[PDB]
Length: 177
Length: 205
Ligand SMILES: NC(=O)C1=CN([C@@H]2O[C@H](COP(=O)(O)OP(=O)(O)OC[C@H]3O[C@@H](n4cnc5c(N)ncnc54)[C@H](O)[C@@H]3O)[C@@H](O)[C@H]2O)C=CC1
Ligand SMILES: Nc1nc2c(ncn2[C@@H]2O[C@H](COP(=O)(O)OP(=O)(O)O)[C@@H](O)[C@H]2O)c(=O)[nH]1
Ligand SMILES: [Mg+2]
Image 1: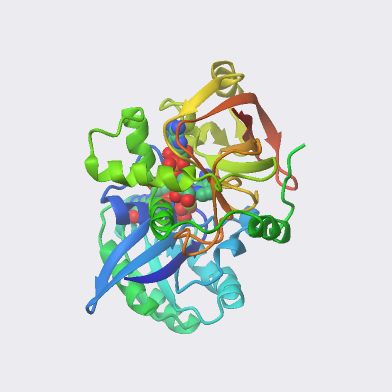
Image 2: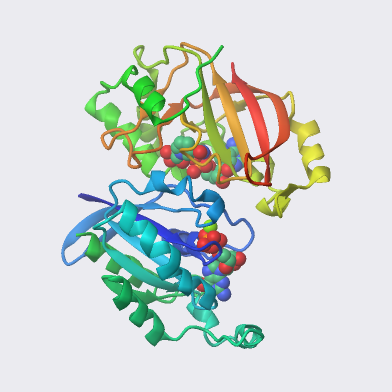
């Protein structure tokens, strides 16, 4: 079996911890949500290869900017996330996340992930984001962004509903090889 | 007096001094736990150390116990080690909101302290820890525990692929059924940030 490492970064509350959980338990968490998810190796096979992918969760807040780097060494792929319900997070992709990664994981393949895809057509979101002259990010924006930052690919998903989740990981896995 | 590692250099140097020649099976058992620890600990706690229900784990546990039981498998000095836990460690009645806006609910905290402070406990599950504080989950969780480990305790130190699926945690793994005493439970503020965190000091007995 092949051993690979995946690290997930992104702004706080953009949905990172939930994504991994749902990836390994087929269960969106509702009452006991860990800030940072535990060690879990995901078993995946794509294009005929069985891979064991260790997943490292991280804290994206500034408070933890000092600690994050201890998770970066020898990474095979990165999941850079933002939330579809938050345009603020997407902007941080270029602003904060891409610069940090290139610095610590210069050649590591990046996969840009739009989380909370279920909030794209959510009235509350829409309206709520309305109060700021912003609306949910459009798919075209993410792809555009991925192209801008040199990502291997771009994906959307919803942990809450599990849409595309399985897809994000498979892709991540391909890029890892 | 127990050693506390300041940085990776110290962490690394202390690490070289430890035992690393486990048997292949020994290495495999340790690495397997690190891949996912939910399976070992959750089961043992649920079953109180009786391994009869799931043979498939029996070998799995019985097997790790040995790696950890070898005579060469102990720690030379008295080292302080650290661990991070979610609020539910203190019972299903609690969650991470216990800390909101960098504040620990005092009413909630005090109940926990009366309940657990000074308590001596036996843990069915293995206890993962880190010699480096910044490594591990100690800063990213609500309750940070510093374990004072007496010399001669039996453990495995892992910071390489052979040993763990997550190199870079500067891990020290203690055996199941280890018993410890909680000396103090308190709230402390983080340097440079304003968030409180629940801090536990416990000693290995
Ligand atoms: N805790 C840390 O900072 C360190 C973690 N690790 C790694 O993490 C894994 C073990 O730590 P966790 O991720 O916390 O898994 P764990 O088995 O220690 O616990 C997982 C979840 O259960 C909770 N829990 C732990 N012990 C409990 C108990 N006695 N009663 C009720 N709830 C309990 C924890 O708070 C956590 O939310 C190992 O795979 C190890 O390699 C390694 C070194 C240090
Ligand atoms: N609607 C919706 N909410 C989500 C989804 N994933 C996570 N959340 C919520 O968004 C918040 C942040 O999630 P979390 O995974 O802790 O974010 P992290 O800090 O980036 O790990 C939590 O309150 C979740 O309830 C999703 O796919 N859809
Ligand atoms: Mg999180």
